Length: 218
Ligand code: NA
Image: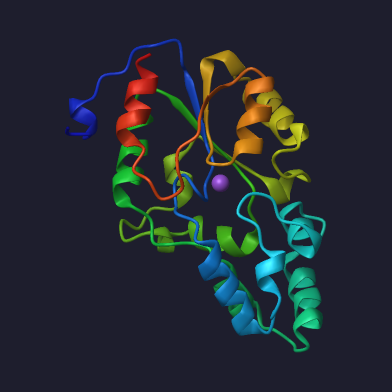
């Protein structure tokens, strides 16, 4: 079938759509991330890095408890050498594959009919790329695809903490039952459901456009 927006029709009680970034808009490859951090000297990266919820200094960075520079310093101490910001950024970008422009185009089409928000565990290294014209070959920052970004490191909590969902709900004024939450992570989906959201859990790396269209018309 043809998933171009002009072919698509939308009608249901859903008014808002909340997307995660990694695992939904852009593919995550944890093995590639592990390799990228090992390159810096983090020889035990395989035990440290997670697909859904970081721990240790990685969590602290994604909750804004460590600044990018502070994280760089503490990561360097683990690696036994002083890291630059650029090589630390490049390690973080190891988590990601280039974006499927089909997904970005689909999301632009959604904005004609829905309020679209991002709610994501992320950090300044990743966002310096995503929230810039370097995000993709289309030259539009992640900001162009949403009404507002809710970023863990600016809010002090990471999903699946209920607090990050609560901030987003209160700030955006969405009614959870009229909102579709799209996230590849099970724990995040479960708390979203508990708080009243409709949920859709796509597979990381999969083309979810068809199924999303079906859900938005259910
Ligand atoms: Na995700």
